[PDB]
Image 1 (tube, rainbow, N blue to C red):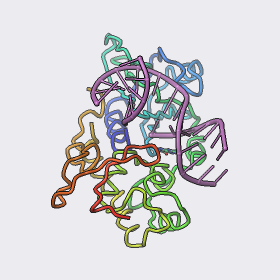
Image 2 (cartoon, rainbow, N blue to C red):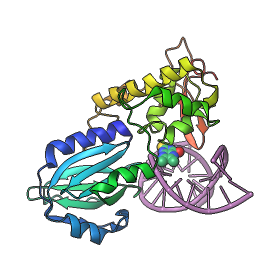
Image 3 (cartoon, rainbow, N blue to C red):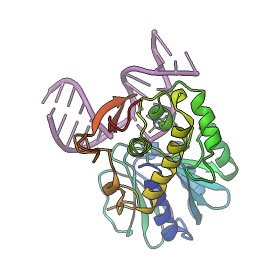
Length: 267
DNA sequence: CTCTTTTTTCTCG
DNA sequence: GCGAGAAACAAAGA
Ligand SMILES: Cc1nc2[nH]c(=S)[nH]c(=O)c2nc1C
């Protein structure tokens, strides 16, 4: 998932598990709890969930006054709310059991992570990762964005994926953003002119906010999304851009599959 | 059978 | 510092 899918999960969880007391925590794959499963089980058992926040693609469970559980779903992580007698599925790894149901984390590829962090360490945790601003008009300052692009010789798509210019773009939405901003994914950022940077800035915000409103792209929480029907380029290799007959091409850029419309996205 | 395909961090040169 | 490649892992397809 990318930011819109994580935000969709965050909103469904906020409606349903806030106020719930954790009765028990169980793991078939404790190694995904990077801070230590036994410690997490000891600290969080019997605590009440006070809220769910998000930073970039990270979910932040607020559990008691003094702990946050930072969860990253990486490539394929999925949460679901199930009855207490729900059967185990093959890639279920962790469960948080409440009195009237349970929250189960599954992840085929086992990439996702849980980290127990004290409340006053949450902001330092994200500072250390150098996560950039949230993709909103209030937080995403174009002036700083422009200065960072001017000072770099990186290609725009890898640089956007690093999460440092702005948080939350992954492979789907960076391809959508560059198509909307008419920018070649291998364009060196110090070559972007001011008017292109402005369109890129606005397009980042508009694509991600539209995706959030449509519930992201897609049985678990967050599989209700409609954004996949509005994708213009991602995963549409060989299909038309609607640009008078031009077809979408797929290349590899810094190891990632990359979908773009060459007519509209020249360097 | 092999090889490729689908977020973050690490190693190498 | 940089880019390239790969590692963590599972499954599906060519
Ligand atoms: C924190 C971080 N996240 C990333 N996420 C993606 S999708 N691609 C990246 O290259 C990347 N790089 C860094 C350093």
